Length: 129
Ligand SMILES: [Cl-]
Ligand SMILES: [Rb+]
Image 1: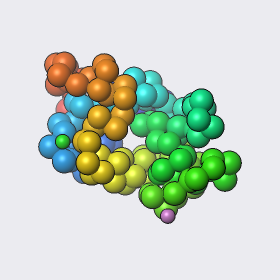
Image 2: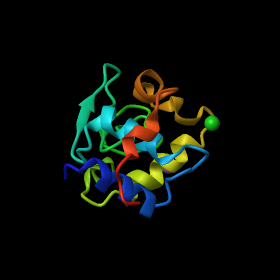
Image 3: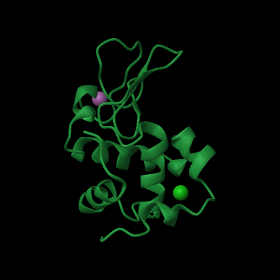
């Protein structure tokens, strides 16, 4: 599923991400935009052999199981394929664990590099939330 901007913001809010660990909704929308372009089916292989999955590009070394990643811990206890669903619950549940791991949203390098410190509220501007 390719979400619309406000559509995703509403779905993230509906799943308790707005202000989760102090990160406003715009932060999450901005991270999704640059990680996946709002496409739940996005997958990207890393140099280390792990793969990133879904709207927030969750990795298969630490977080989900894809059966082909050496040293996988599967800390979200899910198959990585669950992170590609049109329903974002699994991605949101796991992102909550990731953002709680100690480094906040810096866990998403694209968030650090493209969203952190910017006017992230613009990502939810206009939306009926
Ligand atoms: Cl933080
Ligand atoms: Rb596990």
